[PDB]
Image (tube, rainbow, N blue to C red; front, side, top):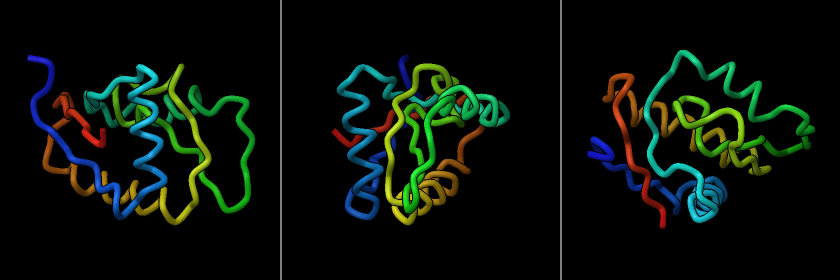
Length: 109
């Protein structure tokens, strides 16, 4: 199998994050997150290298840094901080029901 469970991303609540994820998947970035939480700092170092900060915005990454698929090569987009921080908290809580190694297909479309 390709994935273990599916997650329908809450695009109505966090539309800017959702739009990024949708576009990134249509650009060939992985739609499955193989959860690997320990590596997330190293993966952010890699994905964000050389990308300046912008006020009012966070640098959103897809694939996410908490996934094996993240890090080097990830799509990065400036997303309003409230949208991105809300999405981040939502995802961390929702995925807290799944052990590391679980493969989650994200669907936004």
